[PDB]
Amino acid sequence: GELAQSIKELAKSIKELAWSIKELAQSIKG
Amino acid sequence: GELAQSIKELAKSIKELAWSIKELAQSIKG
Amino acid sequence: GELAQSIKELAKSIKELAWSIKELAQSIKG
Amino acid sequence: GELAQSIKELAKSIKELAWSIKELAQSIKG
Amino acid sequence: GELAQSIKELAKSIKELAWSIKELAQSIKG
Amino acid sequence: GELAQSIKELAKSIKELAWSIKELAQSIKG
């Protein structure tokens, strides 16, 4: 149901956060 | 129920954080 | 119940910290 | 149950991450 | 079922976020 | 069975997340 649906949305948001953190790590090196 | 609603709010707030981290990275780069 | 209320409060804090990070990124740019 | 308690623990860690990113941005702004 | 499947993807996304944060920490320390 | 193993993988990923955020704080402060 909607519990599982909401957890899939949360997982997708966490993947987007992990990508932004990789971008920040690269920008710190220049 | 309200648990599923709170998880969806958390997912939207994490997406907001990911976008702000992407902007921070570009500012350090430029 | 209690756990869903807590998750919603934490989501709001994360959202507000995201807004603050974006403001800092904006002034690092100039 | 345990599922909601784990989501709450995750949200606490994400909030702590956002505070660390803010302090990183502040140190770079100087 | 769907609930187990959604929690799998959630756990794997959190593992990827943890790895990205370690990469950030190492970039910051230099 | 499969849901039970979901939960346990989620719990381990959240401990790894917590450890990585401690590393991030130490690198910022150093």
Image (cartoon, coloured by chain):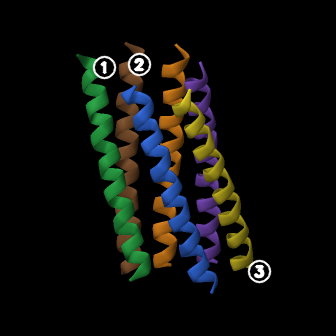
Chain colours: A orange, B purple, C yellow, D blue, E brown, F green
Quickly name the residue at label 2: E3
Dot 1: element: helix
Dividing the picture into quadrants, the one containing residue C30 is: bottom right
Circle 2 packing at 10 Å, graded few (<14), some (14-19), many (20+), is: some
Which mark is on residue F3?
1
The mark closer to the camera, 1 or 3, is 1
Q: Which residue lies furthest to the bottom in this view?
A: D30
Q: Distance between the residues labelled 3 and 2?
A: 47 Å
Q: How far apart are marks 1 and 3 (CA)?
A: 50 Å
- Residues tagged by mark 3 and mark 2 found on one chain of the structure: no
Question: Residue E16, position in %: x, y?
Answer: 37, 48
* Residue A5 position (above or below residue C20): above
For the residues labelled 3 and 2, say whether their Cβ atoms are less than 8 Å apart: no
**Host chain of mark 3:** C
**Identity, as a three-letter code, of the amino acid under mark 2:** Leu
Q: Nearer the viewer, residue A8 or D1?
A: D1
Answer left or right for D26 relative to F3. Answer: right
Quickly name the residue at label 3: C30
**Identity, as a three-letter code, of the amino acid under mark 3:** Gly
The mark closer to the camera, 3 or 2, is 2
